[PDB]
Image (cartoon, rainbow over all chains, first blue to last red; front, top):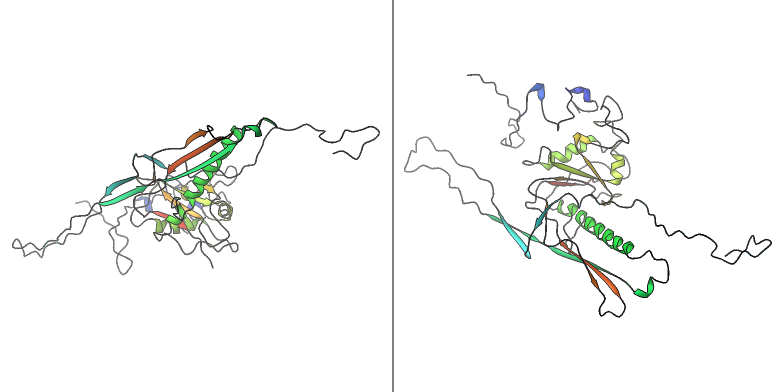
Length: 50
Length: 299
């Protein structure tokens, strides 16, 4: 439906090596510690340097 | 017999042609599932082993209660759960009499021996696909139905097809909960739904925009990069079950104390040479989670 839908041209060339998320070139790390579907969060981003 | 033409001399009576002793036969059912499971040797009636559970939750303190008393969780000592395995038996027998092969055309003996093992291989595969439990294994369809592993819905039954690349994800997003993901899995598709999973139009499509030079030479199938296993041991033409996924890990290991044994009887049967073939095996797994068999439902 996006990215690799009808057309594989929606991405870098992933097909290959096993359908891993590389959203904007960043690896996505799964965490099965989020609560059920409600008013809760599902996608969290963190930037650190110090 | 011969009776027309018979001009002008006597064209015998019958039996006027060369006989072909050469047997040939069609591509029937193959065996593909009973050849990819880990094998467990054992010398007992049953084998029992111990599986622990996860832990846990610990409640953090109220920041003021530093001793007498600490008000932290009470973690209950996790029970080691037994898992026990049961090895069922089957057998087949065959016989010919010594007076019923020297008369005719000598092509007997390995013909019967191939056929009984071929029949036995089919019965093992058919049982591994489908079971009730009445002395046969609980086959994959009637195992992956007691754990609630089904989707509503994939397509529509014998009319209005729409079983595309999307359905594999819809099945996979129920296959997890909490960790059936990554590689090391295989999916098995019915013969009928293998031809219908070829209208798309998505992913592995009819265009060079959808893929490179991957088919080559007959639209083989590899949705999300996965391998596809073809089999017709699934009963289509109904809102039943015919698409199945299995993950390869610690689990799906088959226990046996014996393989096929083949033995011979004759003394003192009064002119009967008789062959018996026995096997003892079962198909089972540890925990009852991480399989999905669709279903594929309609009305």
